[PDB]
Length: 25
Length: 565
Image 1 (cartoon, each protein chain N blue to C red):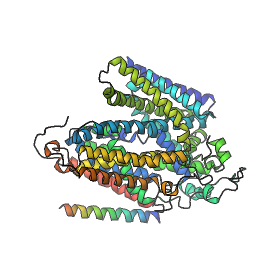
Image 2 (cartoon, each protein chain N blue to C red; image 1 turned 135 degrees about the vertical axis):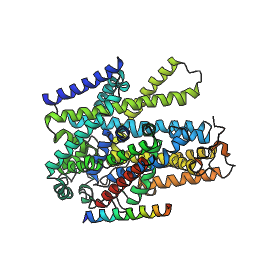
Image 3 (cartoon, rainbow over the protein chains, first blue to last red; image 1 turned 60 degrees about the vertical axis):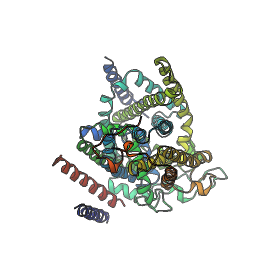
Image 4 (cartoon, rainbow over the protein chains, first blue to last red; image 1 turned 180 degrees about the vertical axis):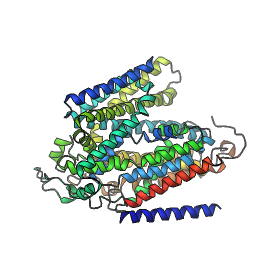
């Protein structure tokens, strides 16, 4: 389904943003 | 089919009110609205709708990568256009590099791109809108458009554009929303559109020219990958490795080097309000999919014989050109679907926007030419001479743009958006690479940057000139252009041109010594904050709120990207 791919992408980018914030910290 | 009292009356009323507003002057919301006003242009409408009708959904990835490039401007390039005290990109380049060769080349390039990607595009889009309404010829349509543009400029509308631009951005968006609703209702809705598009094709696909003969299914059938933004990376309408990467370059050049947006952006109280305006512009830059791209698909569904024309003769009779009627999708939608009353209002607001943009571009081009080319070729100047030169230049660009309408019409298989992006990508990536290198690496010298810019210009002309000389065409009559030169998607050529210009700039700059730091203070991104003077070359919680809003915007953008992947 398409909303599954949308949620997968959202989760992936949220994880990447959290990783970037941790690197900043 | 607008010749009914309901239509002419509203158009006349709208133009009269616009003139009166212009004549009267003779006697977070704003920043984002102004930022999006460029994408609200009717040229953008026509290009996006036509590309959607021709190919599918991928053309919206352009707009959403522009969202991600606006969240690059606000946080990376605006802060440097504020730490350097500079306003426009050419001004930053002059301040950082010095001299005048770079600025003169940038002025000439800006004039060329104004004539090609903006003036000619707006003239052609207005001509298409008028032809699809009054059934006129392209030359008559552009003549009428130019006349109304003259009325606009002389009634003083360009002196009251405040009250005719940022509130016309709500009439061309209410009309866009209403037309999207009407198109979806006519096609059965969201699910109806997505069920029907793939099965919409022309019925007249034989042609009587012996050379053309029978036409293959590949051309009059909608692309199998029409519902996916991620087209094949090699055989695709929008190779996704380019739609993402090779566009971030061109879109960065636009939103970071286009004087209109650069100054509209720097017109913010603080950097935390420029960021908010950019955020709102991004959210509003996600709308063009549903407002223009998918309505173009509905146009192809409802009018296949016209929009999906594949036969050269039928295409000449409908479009006016034998390549294809892709770029009449939105005009057909507007002139057919919407009611007889509001159709006139929609057409009037579209033409008013086109002619306002044309007037603004003419004024900007005249100012640029007079103050950057003739001002140097004749330092004596003189107000009378400058005014005469400006008017003569307006005449010259009008003539050249009118002589370019056939090329705009037949460019990139009749796809206006593809033409715009090809012309951009063939000339922008060089200046984009030079600007990025100047921002980041301080080793760049003035003569090295100029040589890189001119080399990129030459090697991009080596692809722009032959492409237009040999034509582009469609499957039915593919152009006799060299494969190695024409097959590569213009965005892949955009990346190649960017990297070649960067390599050339590095090669030239590495030959000589770097410019000292006294001329780099508060100019390089890595040396913005230094608290030292230069020799020249001639919050606590609001910031967190803005950052979180930017994160929400990126989350929504990636959600939509995955949904339509």
